[PDB]
Image 1 (cartoon, rainbow, N blue to C red):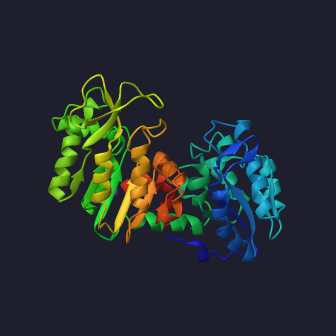
Image 2: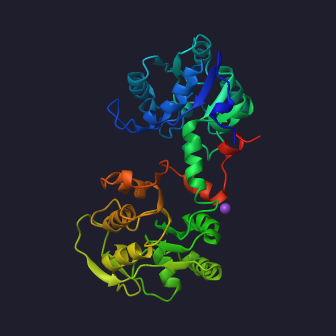
Length: 390
Ligand code: NA
């Protein structure tokens, strides 16, 4: 993969696809972490004598939705880079082109949300050709956008010499340690409500790991297939055979699997609702398992002892509804407490859990909040990565 130093930025206007998809409220960025993380790439290019045009998505609006304008992000960026300016013009527009052509060495221009362009998500080749007028070289520094063939990710990269920025490279390398020669014992903790959403990553990682811990509602599909009585717990009836086959593959590959022993159940998903603890294989109707129980949390933590690599993605229960978030928080706490293990966390709820444990710095790598990381682990590559090779 072509990396940042392969580009000679001197006297060139460089187009950079960054990830500034940050939380915004009342016209103010609520967390500028993503903006800060993009700085090394920008500083390198500016020190190299280039001018910069920045492109980013914000939310997933289908067109020019003012709620998702990058204006607030431009303000936050300028506070760190005084030479940066924001222009409220879609990147495929003639106004954007003129603004970009007027830039001088050292200047930085952030254009409007790429999602405002109708051809962006369609990877419109003509739109990509217009993006190609914005710079002489292209730097992709947004791993979280690399899983989709979009005009500002793949399309323009095919018209300009393309390179991976510092951040993009860092993310790819971290996840690559979960695919190539990972340190063993290697344990994987997967959660989520449906096994169907984990089939790809499970089949991809099974031949590479030693232990697989399964939590979340998807565990009930496995448990029912194995003969357990899960009461009114969520189950994908059309995936019962598949669940059993995945366990069969684990047995064939020498991967030890762990499933819940007990669960915290309730008659309905309600915050603070009264609960009952039942064996995961004996949940009486009308109860439904909503989180892994205390014995399961303990067992899952013990299963990680000795691991040198741990990858975790997914909630252990109904994370957004207390007290059914305890299992997820407990797994995060257990992983943070490990010694001698490279730990990687991905997934919406699990990353959210890590962010409120007050132990985030304890993890080896917390992947980009999105689906790109999981797709990369399943396929071994991404569209945005392929345009940086060759
Ligand atoms: Na794979």
